[PDB]
Image 1 (cartoon, rainbow, N blue to C red):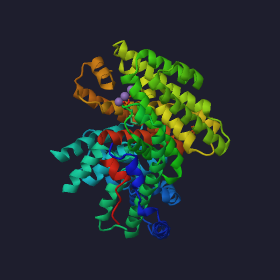
Image 2 (image 1 turned 120 degrees about the horizontal axis):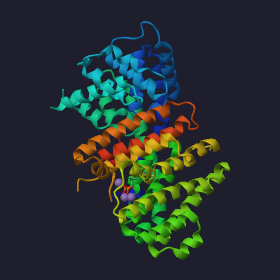
Image 3 (image 1 turned 90 degrees about the vertical axis):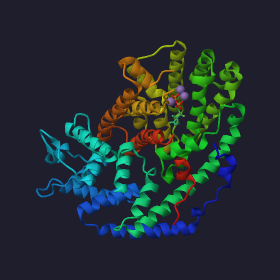
Image 4 (image 1 turned 180 degrees about the vertical axis):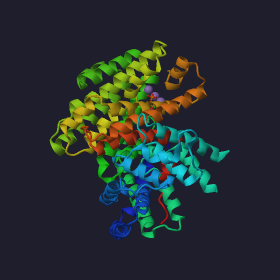
Length: 508
Ligand SMILES: CC(C)=CCC/C(C)=C(\F)COP(=O)(O)OP(=O)(O)O
Ligand SMILES: [Mn+2]
Ligand SMILES: [Mn+2]
Ligand SMILES: [Mn+2]
C-alpha cells in the first residue's frame, strides 16, 4: 500500500514521447518484412512462439494468422509428420490456441501402449508439457502426456537454466498466463540468445515501456476518482487497493484500446473489495439483508432511508458509478445496459449473502453446493459482464443475452477462479479446502493437491467451449473470461511483481 495517490501523480515516464512512438512504427515495418523471410514451418512456429511470449502478438495478428492457416493446410501432408517431440508439441499447442483442429493422435508415435511415453529430451518434454494444457475432456493421450511430463519435470529438482524452465512450467504453464505477465522475463531470455533478432528484441522493449507509460497515465485518472469518493477516509478498512485492482484489469485486457475497460474494471474490483469486506467481516446479518435489498431495488431514496451510516456512502458510490457506466455506454453507442449490469451486481451481492448466512448458521456445505454459490461470489459472472459492456463496441444484444443465460464457459471458468482463490488461504467461514476435507477426510495437503487437479480438469471443459465456433461469444469476449482466470493463477503465485510490471521500465 505504498503506491498512494501522491506517488501515482508524480510519475512522468519518458516513453509517452512522440519520438518513441515513431521509432515503434519504424520497427514494426522492418519486423514485418523480416517475417516474410521465415519460410521454414518450424522456424515459423518458433517465430509465433517468440512473438506471443514477447508481448508483441497483437501487433502482427494477420501475419500470425497467415502462418498458422498455411501450416494447417499442410499438416495433413504425407511427409509433414516428423518424429520430433518438440516440433510436434509446438505445432499442436499453437494450432489449438488459435482454434485450429488438431488430433491428439499426433503424439501416438511417441507413446508405447505398454510402457507409455518414450523420451529423454528435455526440450521435447517441456514443449509436450505445455501442449498438454490444451487437452480436451477424454483425450487419454494428452492426460497421459501430462502425467509423464509432470513427473519428469519434478525430477528435474531432486544446466542451471534447465531447472528454471522446469520450475516455471510447473508453477504456471503458458496456457495459464496472460500475455504481458511473462513479457519481462522472456525479453531477458530472448536477449541472451545467439539467434535473437535484434530488431524484434528492441521492439519488445520499446512496446513494453510504452505500455507502462499508458497504464501510469490511466492510473493517475483512476487514482483521482478514488480519492474523490473518499471511501478510504470513511471506512478505516477501505485500504487503498487501487494498484492491486488495476493489476487485475491489466491482466484482463492489456491492449491500449481497452483503456475504458480497465478503468471500469479497476473501480469495480475496488468496490467489490470494499463490499466483500462488509459481507464477511464488518456487517451484521440484518445490515447485509438491507444492503442486499437496496441493491435489488436499485432505489437511492430507499437506500438512503434504510441503510446504516457506514453503508450509505458505500452504496451510493456503487450506485452512481454503475449509473455513470450506463450513461457512458448510452452516450457512446446508444445501447441501454443498466438492467444487465445491475442484474449482475445483484447476483454477486446475493451470493455474498448466502455465504454470510452459512457462516452464522455454522453450516459446512458440500463442495459442489459451495462451488455453485462460490462461482458467483468470486465475481466471475460480474467481471465478464463488466468486461463485455465496457470493452465491446458495438455491443451485440444476442451476445449479451448469452452471458446472462449463465453459459457453461462462464460456469467452469468461475469455478476455477473460486477454487484458485480458495487455495490462497493459509493453513491457519469454510472454503473449498475445508469443504473437501470435511467431505473426504483427506488432509489439508492432499486436499490442496486434489483441488489443484480439479482446476486442470475444468480447464479441459473450458478448452472445449473456447473451440466451439458456434457460440454467440466472439473470440475476443472469451479472452476476457480466460484472462481473468489466468490472473487468479498468477496472483496465487505472487501473493513485488506488480511494481515491476507497472512502474519499472526495461532499460533500453
Ligand atoms: C475481485 C477480483 C476479480 C479480483 C480482486 C482480488 C480478489 C479475489 C478479491 F478482492 C476478493 O477477495 P476475497 O479473497 O476475500 O474473496 P472471497 O471472500 O469471496 O474469498
Ligand atoms: Mn467473501
Ligand atoms: Mn473476503
Ligand atoms: Mn478468498
